[PDB]
Image (cartoon, coloured by chain):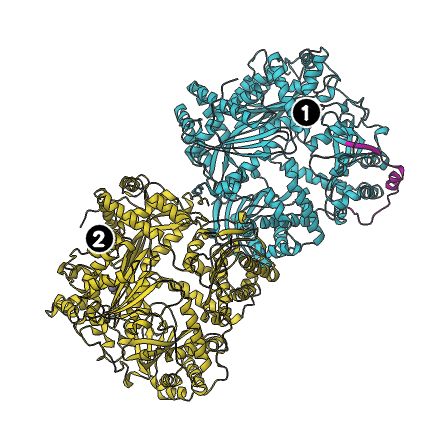
Chain colours: A yellow, B cyan
């Protein structure tokens, strides 16, 4: 009795009783699986389509095809032949899109204003119906892909990824190179007279079949309205009845096992990777055997494998569990980072792993463990935070390929039967004879003889000697390991407290003392049993010089290192914390189920106040911290650019260079002395937000205060005697340039900042609307058309109460060239703005309005919004509505005069600074530009300029 | 064979062989005594005339007449009838004048450009020849005198001064009131039909006789040229042959002795004053009996009376010795300040004094002591710093009344015969039966029954009970007192080191390390055996908050308290030091004979590095420091004004209020911990200047460095990681006002500041030339004519590399009235500047030029000049010549446009701040003024304004 285009309708989708969204699953006649989500409150609608095809289906001779195909779909269809019709449509309607390609999936997703779902969905639909694959774009777009590959080339994590593939069965599609590059997608095909367009076409035509598609749509419309919409657009996707690709034979056969790999890293990291090929456990998902094992082997704290490796001083962290491979095969991994001692005892570390493993084989599957994970996952599912539409649809679209419509939401959370046999079955794979081992360290440099061809990774490959293997097999039973004890952080009280009669819409100051200032709001819209607790501890000793900065950091690092064990239970139990040093002191934040927060917070605080440093932990953390600093040189050029601009523009800021040099002066006794000093006088400013009453909030603050007082004899620090850092004020018509060399990458990174003014309602919206207007043309001009690089970013930069327009680019091309093109782009944006209809202009205002008014869907997000106002000392909780009202009054002329005053090459109030990070080895008309003054010493540079006021609060 | 106008010529004046000035003494026929000083290098010439008449010669019914007469002489003579002819002449020729009246002297003095000595001396001469005593001025000027008295009314030191007089013989002229006021000089005389003008005339005519005059003149001209000059102008002063006043009978007879006075102070001070009437010892000056006694009784450190009173915790400081009375009588005094314990043990303190005294009577005069003082004074005289002309002439003119022409310079330094009998004679006066005692404390408030009539001082007068007196008489011998041991700081090496081949004209950076930066110059022009050693120790812990500021202060106070004893010998031996906390850390400076500097510096440094705090000293210093803070409220309104403007204009600055509140949190353990922290990391910047070689300079720096390293394990602090404080940048056309109440005085104090710009050669000279131009009209308009108060000051204000025009006034009238008159004055200065000849304008430029180019005459002064450049981090050692060259290029138009740009009521770049300090109880056309924004919170005020850059160094 259905619409003839619908094979089946699932009207009972299992969801959480907490979830007010309405859900209907469909199975279209053409095979498409569909989850429709009706949310009448949502400000943004969203859709995602997942093609169950990916890079593993690339033709042998055109590796990267499935990825290039992804890129191309954005760039024109027969119905919508404009190359950025899609992206320009989304931009002008508060929307955004993205997509990715893995081995078996290509997932495309967008969100958009709820009033324009049909229009966006319609343009989106055409990708799977009538792409153009325009030869004009094909040549240009290949660059973005190549640039995207070059982005990753020097990234350790992408290097390892690809190298594990090149070390398997060469025959197996697992071995193929996914990303592609100019060579694979252009050069090699041309040498050999192969038309990659005929190929994109043939690919799209053989694999882009309705029977391998899954869709998820979230809108305001009724499930019924949505159903007709989806059928209307998608029911006519051709079903090619292509068989779902399958990979039964494991890419790692015997001649690939019992192998050792010595790898040269880009960063100076010490890492041990231990891998076991396992069968695909996807089918056994309602008992989840690999995670049961992942949970135990990767467990942290008391008795765990990690505690031990930590105590011996070999390893700092550990990750264990199941790793996805592809339909037919998976991996089970144990990865750890190595201390200097660790690197010399790899063979024993591996022995200790097998001992832990042995204990499990002897002990057997534990009913209670599985039952505890089960109980946790269930609470997690029921009280799961409301998701952002874009991430939610994209995720669901992916999940539809693996689970019944009615189980698509609960799958991967809700376990059912315990299956001891399945656990045992996997456990049997975990053996020396089945192991691959990879050591990553610069202590291998110069002494490898192999180059992976896509990344150029340097490595040695050798067989683990039998005497070793056998030692591992003969791994006995270490009485030092032992099973996790019961989780006592498991929440039990989920009662949502009645809203108090006094409850406020925004956080209210309910305590204003010398020692503590306390902002509190009781949750009035999400109603989950969660709280967010944030504390900023202010002390001048935290940032007085590079040495105290180094000392505050190491103090927290060591505190966290000391708490891990105990806190790991809480983390499993959905109760998490973060602790970090700031330029004002320390930042402590607790989030999760409110129930047992007092227990963790009390322990955290008592801990800081009574901290006794272990000498060995100290020396290890400090070594790591040292490497961490040096390691910054291996970071992306664009991240260097953003880093130095930050340091440049703030009154006081210690560089990684200053910190490294002052680090040697840090010693255990000096640090020991430092702690009490740091703790002796403090001011605290807090936001306690969620399922809590005023009464409870104050009780929490008091525990924290009184704890510090009794254990570190803390006394108040008057807020008025706390210095706050100002932003550097650039001169009218000034242009400064700061130049550094990136010693790792062959791309340069540039950040161009045009300082405007102190933040205020008017200035903010001039800036943000101008940004909104150029946001997508920036992408379309500098990346799509000019193809200057994969990383091309424009937008608002805010700090220390000041703001301005920033551009960020990572490019093969040099900084002075980027500059000109950016300036060439600005001229263009001006004219485009003059020649803009009042209608296109109103769209943009409406676009930015929806983006700003789009409310947080969860507590932690709303909490972070509030925390931003507190941290900045602006306390502007109604900022969104006030700022959007002003925004709607702006006209084209407002924006023109703004640009001419602050942004034009010849603007009287142009305040430009550029940060050029040079690659290791270093069209529309661009204007003539002044000669920049070049900064050689950041300190001198700041001394010779004025500083801004601090923003007034509300 | 002399000029007939000269009775005698002394051509052998005893001077120091070091002194290149030429000296001739004359005795004019008319009785005038004269010292002529030829100095061909001097940039400024100078004269002083001392009339051996003062307030003790005031007529009974017009007290203050001799003082009013002084004032009036400045205001017109028959030859030069213009009321400010004199002062305007000096101003326009780089000169200045002042005068004072004591009991027996009226001393008038001026300096002026060396090229205009005759013209100035000529106008000056007329004061003693043909004053006008103009009725128009007489009425106006009385105000200045009254205002001058009101300035002093609330000053404890002037209150006590006058009260000791009102407590003597009422018959004796000593009892008269010196300053005068509107009442004595106008009101009472009018009630009783007495013409004070007939009186000024009669006074001048009976007492202003050549036979009571002494003159001293210092010029470039030859002694012969000077002789003719002096005779020309002064030989015709009428000799009235008036007998020199004499006061043989002591103003304190028996019925005035054995008295006790309980006095109520304005400040909260605890002071004990012990006084003995002695005979006049003026005649015994070449053995100096009262100073021999003054030296011993006032001695500090080992064995001394003070050490003991200190150890018992009663007294913090002590002053003892002879005090001038007037021809015929003197006093011998012992004054101490009291701790809280001290105030309850006054009677025992006094007993301990008499015990020390007893020891002296038993021990008898000590030949070696007198001989040691003798040797010291002789070195002091020989190596005396070259004096500034104005202070030198004024002093000499006074000295001529007491000593042979040929002994006028050496007198009071060079002793001759030891006279044991004279010592004994004075010592006999020092007895309980001859003592007056005065306790000054707020613990007397409300319970006195006497009012001194001139100051209104509140006090009780009672007779020391005989049982007490007798106890003092029965004072035995305390074995705890003991005679000063030999002074080992007595210098012995006076060799002046040859100037090195490399010697530089300005200090040169001869060391530039992480830990120490060292500026050094070898003296190339004074050639005395002296050095100046200045160290600024930089540490952030010194000013991080009010508590650390309080802690750095108390640390130094206690260090100095602990060193006194040991260092007092060095001080006697012309080797002095200063130690004080600064906003950047600590400041240490040593000056004097270079010989034994290393000994003192070594001891000072070792001391800081190894300081062990005594608990009792701590509690006492801290009490004092507490009182010190509160006591600030009793300071002059104009000093409050200058104080709050300073705090207002600097980025960071703790108020006396913040410091008092944070003081309670200071404790011995907290302070003990603070010291090592403070000393652990340091940067040092030093100027070592004088009779020292490069080699020696570096050796001194190294001792200081290595001392700290070995005793407080100091490590370097990178100069680049040291934050420096910026000045607040006021907005264009802004006007802020900060208002406070002075709770003691009945005058208000105002400081008006017009911020101009960052310092630079051009800006500096615009400012200083404008100041030079208005300097004297300011005085003549606001004080002389408008009579707004005694304190009326205009000039340049410099700080944190910024500058501006400041006006300071203390007035009966309210702040808003002062403001208008000041603004009324500015309009006037503008027109006056437009209507100014190029000739009057060039004079002003030439005036300011001479003032700026006038070189230091001694080492410590040149050293302070250099230190200013270092402390400010401008290092502009040639500043004077460079700035004067620019100054000579300026024109009237330059100054006009400057005024219109920065200073006019409607100037676009007017940056005005005012500080109004309200009295306890609160014509040319003034412009309309804006409504000021009023500052209620200095902190908020600074946060909302930008900050200036720091000046670039050279
Ligand atoms: Zn891509
Ligand atoms: Zn006077």
Q: Which residue is mark 1?
A: B400
Say the numbered circle drawn on residue A781.
Answer: 2
Per the image, label 2 sits on a secondary structure element best described as: helix
- The image quarter containing residue B676 is bottom right
Residue at far left of view: A193
Asked whether mark 2 and ligand 1 are closer than 8 Å, the reply comes as no
Q: Quadrant of ligand 1?
A: bottom left
The quarter of the image holding the N terminus of chain B is top right
Residue A690 vertical placement versus A322 (above, below):
above
Relative depth, front residue between B126 and A378: A378
Q: Are marks 1 and 2 on the same chain?
A: no
Which residue lies at the image location 74% right of the left edge and 34% below the top edge? Answer: B264
Which chain hosts label 1?
Answer: B
Residue at far front of view: A1
Q: Which residues are magenta?
A: B459-485
Q: Position of residue B930 (x, y in %)?
A: 47, 28
Q: Position of residue B943 (x, y in %)?
A: 48, 43
Which chain hosts label 2?
Answer: A
Q: How many marks?
A: 2
Pointers 1 and 2 in contact (C-beta within 8 Å): no
Q: Residues within 10 Å of mark 2 (few under 14, many from 20)?
A: some
Residue A688 vertical placement versus B526 (above, below):
below
Q: CA distance from mark 1 to mark 2?
A: 93 Å
């Amino acid at each position: 009795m259905n619409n003839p285009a619908i094979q089946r309708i699932e009207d009972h989708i299992v969801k959480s009783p907490e979830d007010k969204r309405e859900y209907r699953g469909l199975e279209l006649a053409n095979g498409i699986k569909v989850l429709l989500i009706s949310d009448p409150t949502t400000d943004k609608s969203s859709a995602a389509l997942d093609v169950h095809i990916g890079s593993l289906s690339d033709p042998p001779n055109i590796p990267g095809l499935s990825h290039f195909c992804e890129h191309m779909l954005f760039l024109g269809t027969k119905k919508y032949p404009k190359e950025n019709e899609y992206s320009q449509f989304l931009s002008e309607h508060a929307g955004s899109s993205n997509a990715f390609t893995s081995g078996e999936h290509t997932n495309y997703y967008f969100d958009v204003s709820h009033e324009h779902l049909e229009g966006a969905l319609d343009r989106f639909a055409q990708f799977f119906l009538c792409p153009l694959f325009d030869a004009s774009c094909k040549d240009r777009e290949v660059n973005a892909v190549d640039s995207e590959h070059e982005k990753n080339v020097m990234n350790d994590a992408w290097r390892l990824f690809q190298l594990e593939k090149a070390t398997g069965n060469p025959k197996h599609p697992f071995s193929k190179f996914g990303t592609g590059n100019k060579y694979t997608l252009e050069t090699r095909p041309n040498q050999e007279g192969i038309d990659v367009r005929e190929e994109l076409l043939k690919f799209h035509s053989t694999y882009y079949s309705s029977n391998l598609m899954a869709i998820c749509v979230l809108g305001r419309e009724s499930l019924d309205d949505l159903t007709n919409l989806v059928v209307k657009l998608f029911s006519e996707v051709e079903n090619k009845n292509v068989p779902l690709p399958e990979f039964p034979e494991h890419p790692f056969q015997e001649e690939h096992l019992k192998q050792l790999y010595k790898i040269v890293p880009i960063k100076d990291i010490r890492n041990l990777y231990v891998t076991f090929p396992i069968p695909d456990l996807q089918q056994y998902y309602k008992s989840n055997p690999g995670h049961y094992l992942g949970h135990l082997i990767g467990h942290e704290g008391p008795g765990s494998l990690l505690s031990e490796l930590k105590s011996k001083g070999w390893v700092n962290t550990l990750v264990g569990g199941q790793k996805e491979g592809a339909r037919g095969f998976m991996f089970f991994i144990i990865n750890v980072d190595l201390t200097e001692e660790g690197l010399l005892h790899v063979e024993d570390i591996i022995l200790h792993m097998f001992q832990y493993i042995q204990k499990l084989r002897a002990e057997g599957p534990q009913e209670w463990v599985f039952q505890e994970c089960k109980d946790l996952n269930a609470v997690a599912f029921r009280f799961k935070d409301k998701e952002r539409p874009r991430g939610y649809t994209s995720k669901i679209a992916g999940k539809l390929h693996y689970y019944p419509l009615n189980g698509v939401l609960t799958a991967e959370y809700l376990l059912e039967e315990f299956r001891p046999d399945l656990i045992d079955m996997v456990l049997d794979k975990l053996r020396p004879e089945n192991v691959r081992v990879a050591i990553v360290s610069k202590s291998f440099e110069g002494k490898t003889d192999r180059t992976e061809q896509w990344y150029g990774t340097q490595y040695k490959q050798e067989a683990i000697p039998e005497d070793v293997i056998q030692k591992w097999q003969n791994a006995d039973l270490n009485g030092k390991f032992k099973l996790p004890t019961k989780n006592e952080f498991i929440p039990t009280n989920f009662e949502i407290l009645a809203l108090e009669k006094d409850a406020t819409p925004y956080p209210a100051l309910i305590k204003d003392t010398a020692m503590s200032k306390l902002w509190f709001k009781q949750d009035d819209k999400f109603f989950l049993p969660k709280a967010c607790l944030n504390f900023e501890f202010f002390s001048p000793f935290a940032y007085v010089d590079p040495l105290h900065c180094n000392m505050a950091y190491l103090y927290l690092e060591l505190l966290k290192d000391s708490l891990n064990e105990y806190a790991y239970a809480a983390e499993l139990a959905g109760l998490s914390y973060d602790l970090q040093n700031t330029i004002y002191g320390m930042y402590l934040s607790v989030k999760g189920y409110n129930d047992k927060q007092p227990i963790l917070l009390k322990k955290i605080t008592e801990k800081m106040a009574t901290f006794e440093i272990d000498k060995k932990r100290f020396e290890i953390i400090k070594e790591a911290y040292m490497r961490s600093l040096n390691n910054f040189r291996a970071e992306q050029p664009h991240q260097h650019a953003m880093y130095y601009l930050r340091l440049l523009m703030t009154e006081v800021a210690w560089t990684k260079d200053e910190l490294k040099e002052a680090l040697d002066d840090v010693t255990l006794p000096r640090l020991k002395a430092f702690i009490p000093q740091l703790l002796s006088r403090l001011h605290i400013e807090a936001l306690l937000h969620g399922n809590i009453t005023k009464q409870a909030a104050l009780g929490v603050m008091q525990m924290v205060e009184d704890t510090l007082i009794e254990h570190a004899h803390t006394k108040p620090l008057l807020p008025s005697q706390l210095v706050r850092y100002r932003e550097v004020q650039l001169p009218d018509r000034g242009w400064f340039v700061y130049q550094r060399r990136n010693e790792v990458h062959n791309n340069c990174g540039i950040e161009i900042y045009y300082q405007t003014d102190m933040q205020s309602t008017s200035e903010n919206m001039f800036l943000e609307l101008f940004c909104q207007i150029i946001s997508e043309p920036c992408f379309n001009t500098l990346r799509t058309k000019e193809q200057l690089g994969y990383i091309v970013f424009s937008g608002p930069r805010r700090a220390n109460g000041i703001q301005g327009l920033r551009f960020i680019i990572q490019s093969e091309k040099p900084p002075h060239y980027l500059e000109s093109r950016v300036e060439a782009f600005l001229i263009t944006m001006e004219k485009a703005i003059e020649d803009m209809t009042e209608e296109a202009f109103q769209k943009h205002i409406q676009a930015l309005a929806i983006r700003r008014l789009d409310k947080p869907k969860k507590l932690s997000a709303e909490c972070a919004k509030y925390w931003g106002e507190i941290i900045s000392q602006q306390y502007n909780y109604d900022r969104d509505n006030i700022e959007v009202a002003y925004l709607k009054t702006l006209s084209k002329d407002d924006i023109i005069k703004f640009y001419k005053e602050m942004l034009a090459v010849d603007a009287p109030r142009r305040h430009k600074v550029s940060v050029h990070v040079l690659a290791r080895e270093m069209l529309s008309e661009a204007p003539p530009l002044p000669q920049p003054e070049v900064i050689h010493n950041m300190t001198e540079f700041k001394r010779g300029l004025p500083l801004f006021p601090l923003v007034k609060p509300h």
